[PDB]
Image (cartoon, rainbow, N blue to C red):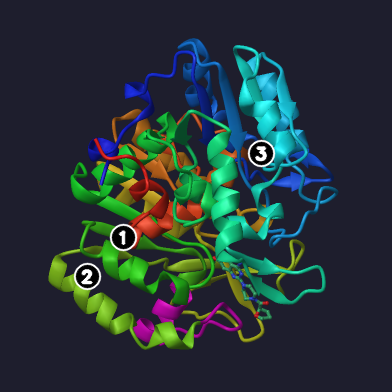
Amino acid sequence: MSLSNKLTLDKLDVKGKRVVMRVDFNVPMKNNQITNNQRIKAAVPSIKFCLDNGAKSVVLMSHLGRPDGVPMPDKYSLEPVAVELKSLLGKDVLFLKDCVGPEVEKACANPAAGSVILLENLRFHVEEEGKGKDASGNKVKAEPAKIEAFRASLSKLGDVYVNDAFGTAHRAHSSMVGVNLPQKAGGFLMKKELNYFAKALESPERPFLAILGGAKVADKIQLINNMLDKVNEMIIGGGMAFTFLKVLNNMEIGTSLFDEEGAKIVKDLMSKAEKNGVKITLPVDFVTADKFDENAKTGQATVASGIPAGWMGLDCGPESSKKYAEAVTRAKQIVWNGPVGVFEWEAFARGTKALMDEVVKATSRGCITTIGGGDTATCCAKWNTEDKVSHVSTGGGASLELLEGKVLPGVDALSNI
Ligand SMILES: COc1cc2nc(N3CCN(C(=O)[C@H]4CCCO4)CC3)nc(N)c2cc1OC
């Protein structure tokens, strides 16, 4: 599942070549400024390698948010990323106000040696995703000839193509699968990410522990099912736990998150766990709240006491953290996708923070620890543990596709060796 069969950047001859590189620069924003640059830094090694090995230019392309194929320069512009990238590179970045057309092509045709260029959001064009919404809010499908022309234009921007956009690798979008150049290479971030998950999924050090949390469970079914064939141990925490608790223990869970459809398959999941010899760890106690608010009134519950009606479980308790800690301590490899409580609120972050402490300690004694993207990675940013675990994935949705046993279109479209 690694890039072993695919052309990679390190094997790419880029001296005197223009490199058009798809990156995932879809960073979280607030008020026109970046609040997490993790995805930008993650791409720096590929960019730096190109500049260091005599590349004539590196033309960077990405999307930002979901403008749905309409230009939205005042809401979703990549301009700020240009500024941040220049800061990280110690080098000028030229921002272009479009990503195709004659003028874009002319700026990229033959740039001064060492030029870094960043194009405007790819998704301002419906041809990128192949569908979107018009100015009026009607859903639209892109036209075949225009899609090819969009792709033909992106292709003109470089002599060789690098995809470093792991976070977007599950999207079969034009910049990801439709660039037509003789060499199509995986970048250093693509290789890194794929190497971490490939080992986790094919050849992990064992016991292999999966920590699965976050809110809803229906979207987690094929995920749990698939992981049950890979792991030796699984923590099921956060929002999903209450559906299990209710089915398995007849727990009264108040207004806690509950997934009726998922309830139907919980016993089958547990049978599968048992059959495969997977130890499942569910929480046994909770921090409760009288409503979904950062300031709600709080309380405590266990599985036996139940959660009072009107109240909801928003975090696991001290005893739960203990059991989580024990599974972590046994692990030699860990993939963690989903916090185990409402981490962004102080009253409900103890469990996720405590788990993070264990995962860092686990890393310190040699455990391979993989943090999926999304909220979990945000937690790493929040508590400054980005360099204290083995790998913080840049791809939450993409890493999830891999954990479910699915293929990544962005990877398959790379040149074969
Ligand atoms: C224990 O772990 C978690 C529990 C979570 N619970 C919730 N909800 C969200 C919304 N909920 C409610 O509004 C209550 C009150 C009205 C409906 O039931 C139910 C509790 N949301 C979340 N986002 C939750 C996330 C969690 O971990 C990440």
Can you say whether 272 is above or below 78 in the image?
Answer: below
Q: Residue at x 24, y 57 (%)?
A: 231
Q: Nearer the viewer, mark 3 or mark 1?
A: 3
- Which element type, helix, strand or loop, lies under badge 3? loop
Could you give the CA–CA distance between mark 3 and mark 1, rounded to whole angstroms? 29 Å
Foreground pick, 220 / 417: 417
Whether residue 66 is in magenta: the answer is no
Q: Position of residue 376 (x, y in %)?
A: 52, 49
The residue where tag 2 is placed is 273
Q: Are marks 1 and 2 in contact (CB under 8 Å)?
A: yes
Q: Please rate how many residues cluster around mark 2, counting C-alpha atoms within 10 Å: few if below 14, some from 14 to 19, many from 20.
A: many
Give the magenta range.
Answer: 241-258
Q: Is residue 99 left or right of residue 252?
A: right
Q: Is residue 296 above or below residue 61?
A: below
Does the CB distance between marks 3 and 2 fall below 8 Å? no
* Distance Cα–Cα, label 1 vs label 2: 9 Å
| Residue 253: in magenta span | yes
Q: Which mark is residue 36?
A: 3
Q: Nearer the viewer, residue 117 or 142?
A: 142
Q: Which residue is identified by label 1?
A: 234
Q: Is residue 23 visible?
A: no
